[PDB]
Image 1 (tube, rainbow over the protein chains, first blue to last red):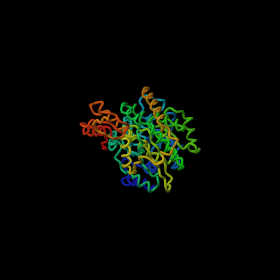
Image 2 (cartoon, rainbow over the protein chains, first blue to last red; image 1 turned 90 degrees about the horizontal axis):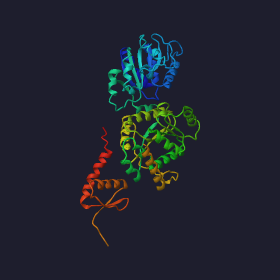
Image 3 (cartoon, rainbow over the protein chains, first blue to last red; image 1 turned 60 degrees about the horizontal axis):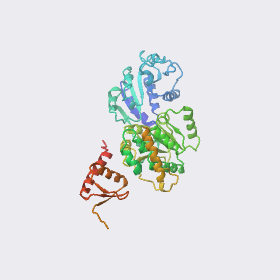
Image 4 (cartoon, rainbow over the protein chains, first blue to last red; image 1 turned 90 degrees about the vertical axis):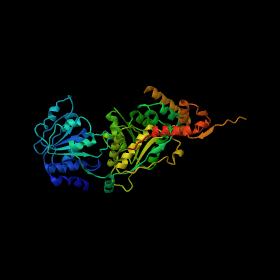
Length: 408
Length: 66
């Protein structure tokens, strides 16, 4: 990829004594730049990942390069540890083992074995936007290499600590424009839309009487939102497009997955039932509408489903929803002629969530993505399968939310 | 046979629930409740209705965009 050589053009200039951040998309080969930089400097490189599936993705790039199972490219884990070598080591570590606190499982001594024998030379950090934290400063203070590098896809955070990375790791060097890279390889053309569903009069007066996190239980469970969700579900099946429904709330995810008759992936779900839906989503065509919480988006992003629906949205994390929504669009690449990646947001009128959802769409204009407004699509008035459309079901939904507010 | 002099204010039912909140606080606002889209407001407070209704939407929407 030419933008990787543009990212590598700064490394070939001065050669020695440099440290910066390179912004590359998730669908782009961001792991390929760390391989060529490891073949240029040739030193003990420690990879700073966060998940075990992030360790296995970097080990496949070592097989594509040169050796991994030898006594050089180690693999730092809390279950087992491997051996490294001098000036030729490619080890991947974990944040919950190198930093830690006191919980050691006979692997903390192995984690400090490469940070005390001068086995460094290159620092590669995965996702630099999470380094604005607290335990990340303990990782940088225990290492002292010659050159550093940070790889990420997004850095928009309102925690007011993203500007601290210019002296900790280094300033940003190459920021590639995502609309320009969408013309290189079509990484799903984004259509940001927000369905302006109306608010019923019974749920509006009960919305103002509730505050805190209990008031979101009346916004998501709005009766016209189920008329807006079931209309967009049946609309995408007529076009032959799979749907991935996002929700920040675990209980609100189950309420939209049980009434629509779809499987769900939520918090503390067993992995035998979690992987069974993925075999019914990637192979079976009957499951084109999945319901995922916050576990099925930060672990594995699906390159299918060109229609995304956001229902439950949390305040504050509107930049965290933008990091989640961006990884789905970067995973969707195959360079199609159309490739219309529709994004919808069922925002009810005069609720406190739609005014924070405008902060989420404002981040997408900064990425170059186009945002449009859709009040109502002319077709939801002809769907008799819309639940909570009749005034009897709206009062039955009102009593279930009023029973929900008494429990919370 | 009886014609009382008020002020007909036609609006949506979501705004209508906000007009009744003004009568629940400062009072002497809504004289009669007609239907789901119409109310009977006192004629001496119609300009006070339009000024107070813009304040509550400015606090509900906010959005500094900065």
